[PDB]
Picture 1 (cartoon, rainbow, N blue to C red):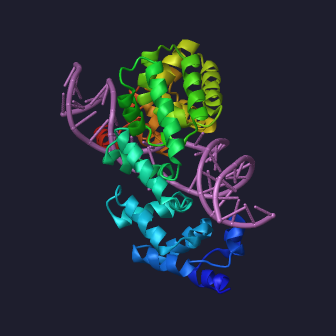
Picture 2: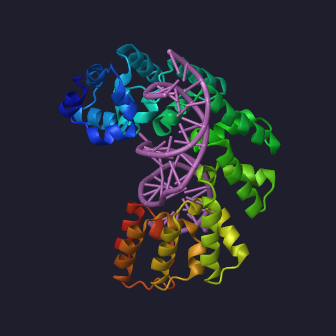
Picture 3: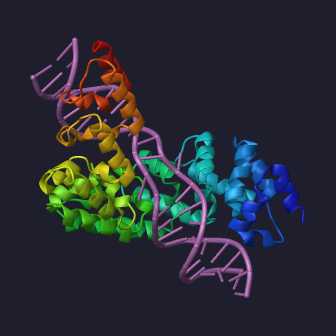
Length: 324
DNA sequence: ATTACCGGGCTCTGCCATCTTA
DNA sequence: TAAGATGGCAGAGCCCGGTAAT
């Protein structure tokens, strides 16, 4: 009845909203006013509230009480109201897509029961909020899948692998077990790779790899192989390089290639590059920016130690002064 | 005094398909 | 038999600085 006019006053993108959840508009009762007041109660700007609703309309169908109990359960994990406003601005659906506050509460029990610390639950929730809308069974699945993979390989107590992984890869619990499995095999296959080596890879420098979508790791490594092969890098060189800096798989193929070229267009050998993988941390902008700075003093780059291209502003800028 | 080695800190969706449920 | 609840998917880095090494 009064619905559409409210949303207009609230600043909502009504057309977008209708298309995302049309069933919300076929309802004889809605709590849009309650919700606005509630969020205003907790710090949220009028604009944010509109954005929120625009993207997840079903939000307006929750009761003040439900909202309050959920919010309080988030406060058992995050410490301030402002921290929660900010999360919801970036990810409304995670808060509003369920209304099962019992299940939420059990997740939290379960996560504690698995040995994670508040510091960690806070980390999950802040970066991977949607963890807390998973059903209990779904969070169990994954956790049991990790435990399994823990003991399937050398690790003495999976309990502590689980934590290492979840700390380093706070996005692990909202990936399918399918996806994660495949990325593990891809790793095992393509490289050495005995249980011990693999474990350290997964908990550490290549933890991101487990979150890559189906066949993306295959296809990015391929492009890495081809691109380096094309430059006279043997396969062995190629492996040592990627195992020493597995992060490089995440880059989009064009981004990797570009980077290689923009360096090498300035007469930096491929050999110089793969022997100092970390230079690829820098953005292309950071790279060319810095490349112009240096050639623009006496440096020839052909024979310079290039580690500095990926140093901090301070260490880099310091060294640049000294070179003029 | 200066570089190497290595690990940390930010990282926070939005959509579509497929069940449940009332 | 329609909404709500849930699972699952593609996407595609950068930067800083403590401490060891020299």
